[PDB]
Image (tube, rainbow over all chains, first blue to last red):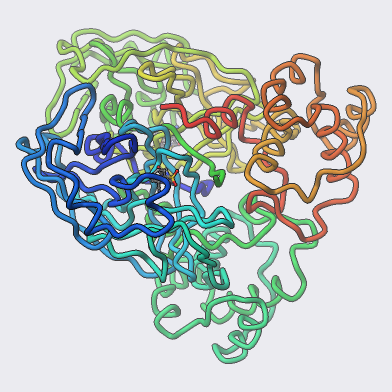
Length: 304
Length: 304
Ligand SMILES: *CC(=O)N1CCN(S(=O)(=O)c2ccccc2C#N)CC1
Ligand SMILES: *CC(=O)N1CCN(S(=O)(=O)c2ccccc2C#N)CC1
């Protein structure tokens, strides 16, 4: 029993973190096989960052300008290329700790673990969600860029995020491991505003199911609703529209608890309209939306 | 910027987790050097658990009854002893991945990371606090016993918790790595009620400092208070008394922000008396008390 914001065990990813230095900029890189992946802004001066031309800046960089350090051992860079907003540094040594891995581009609402790193050294691990506005709400100081987000399916690490940027509102933007930003963000120090940070409805429902399973049941009511009725109330409270796809995904939690998805929608509707009245659900005074249905099943079933 | 509930990187601890089986009970063990540490209740039948006599139950157990598996490789048990509520299983092989380590007994209010495990395999990592009533609020299913809590100082893992028990109220009890329970709990299936779960005041203050540092400032007010005045309001709201020791510990966060500790106490007093009025602080609608002042400095400074 009990339900916690839980990150994946980070050891498989700790084994992949290196330091990348170009001139005076130090950040983190991800070493898989004989390639080190890092943010292309490693090549910029903070001045360059106002209006960088990365192809032009890269011309002035040689393999020997990219200093790659794994622990206190230097790696030999034998190649470099730009793919979108990441650099791929070919090194002469395969990472001996390379886990089974995939590069995946996640959808908004999908959760992942972040291993926050500085100078290629892990400082901590936390659970994030790709927000509907394609930001994440992370914890990232100067030097944390190239820190990665990931899921684990048993022994295969799926890398979904690399950290590149803090917006002036203190929320975070980054790329998949092909260097494509999530959302409309660019690696330039310019006016970039996030859109509406809507609540991930299907994740809130998952978390209400988690609460019921762990004995927090006070919010269950005598009502039901329809997808269309629920969605009227969702729109009004800046919740994402609930689709039949989301309902289908909640099916197993529905089955385990014997609470119809639409009944739990009606509970959530009353919570939105009435508030918590100073009560808590799983130790929170607001409706948590950074657990996927898959997360709730994983934690409630004990997958490794 | 941004402030997250952050666990230590877990790789050093992943490298220590094994499976322990005695008859039909499977749980987790911690392999450091040539010793495997696990809950003594591994030797019980669920029937034994009503009124177990551990010394008597242990007499019927030989070294070869303790099945210890690290990955899919069996370890040879060459000795076993009981220390308080843990078993120490001497094995013929030193754990080659043994990190630098310490056993520490933490005080209530101290935070730590838990690596939740099943069958000696990591499922996830989360941040906990030793509650003032010597429970933790964890996420632990059957098979999670012998999962450990730890802090890391650079390269030295300080083990502070091993998981043993869920109380009928779904909160958790366990031991230090010398097998001494935190609080008054016993490894027996009996009426055990937790005392008052009071709020860790010094941790809330730390977290308010974290909020100010990350730009959440709306709760700062024009007031100050005294330790005695604050403590009257603390008592009334089931907050731990604030001591000059706690004030001294908040000194560095005081200095960084230029907010006198007692001024921040006065902010916290107004929050307790007035509530949040539907506002949030660092994404929470309630006052977070599972960050120590040390945690806030670590995360805000980026220690590895
Ligand atoms: C996340 C991270 O480590 N960084 C992003 C923010 N910068 S920076 O804006 O200070 C900067 C300085 C010099 C050159 C490039 C950049 C960028 N971007 C620090 C690195
Ligand atoms: C945490 C954990 O893995 N366990 C504690 C709860 N038990 S149990 O109560 O089901 C039990 C069954 C058989 C023998 C001993 C115990 C105990 N305690 C499962 C293990």
